[PDB]
Length: 259
Ligand SMILES: Nc1ncnc2c1ncn2[C@@H]1O[C@H](COP(=O)(O)OC(=O)CCCC[C@@H]2SC[C@@H]3NC(=O)N[C@@H]32)[C@@H](O)[C@H]1O
Image (cartoon, rainbow, N blue to C red; front, side, top):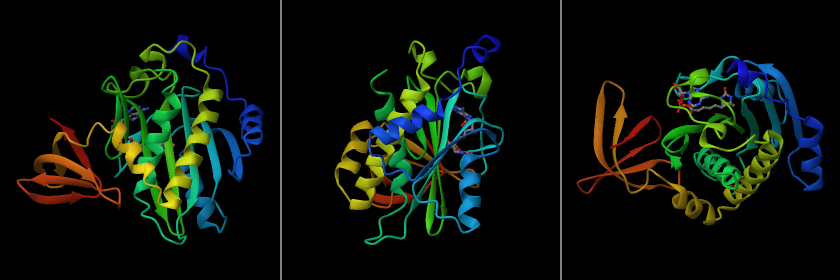
């Protein structure tokens, strides 16, 4: 932790940039900032001021007031995660269901760390060995969605959440955050393209990495309510379809427990 903090090199923005260039990337802007309250908040604020955030990438070394979903938090220490948000214009034509972007983002994270090391837990989680390796948050601000990823690279669970894990804690020796980050951006770009095009590979690939689909689950709803059943599928809006004795309960978000 003290030990870890002293062995976490900064990102090399110029090298991230070079990788996007060499690759002919369609990302329109890439910035790394030392610290911010929330990258998601930052891109939403740009959009709100009339900036075109489509294809804008914002990476923060440190994030001091991270957002989870529905009012929960996201914790970090400096240089220990890849903390990034991207803008996506969603009002195209033929309009696709923006609820799939968060799923596409998880998928891209898992594909980016596959070379080094389990799967996607709906709605927001990337798990490895049952621990939370990454969290995904998509926020709509028509005509945009801001899509956020917190990926634990060397972050220790004692620094952020007892149920967290990281690439380092999974046994990856000296993870190269630059190379992972560049790979992540390549895969996010690829999945957003599939999403726009209504390409079926997206949902097929998500299924192939899904921990939730096919599981006995409890869906937990406000008011201490719950519904227990089988996570039958994810629908074309990105929502979980729970089979309860033949009847379908479709939930758009919120908490899901694998039993
Ligand atoms: N670093 C971490 N690693 C694993 N778990 C964590 C964590 N920090 C917090 N947690 C736990 O995970 C919960 C939140 O999980 P949820 O499913 O609600 O929420 C999520 O998993 C979505 C997390 C989104 C983070 C990215 S970072 C870049 C962008 N900017 C932001 O401000 N947010 C996005 C917290 O209540 C903690 O229990």
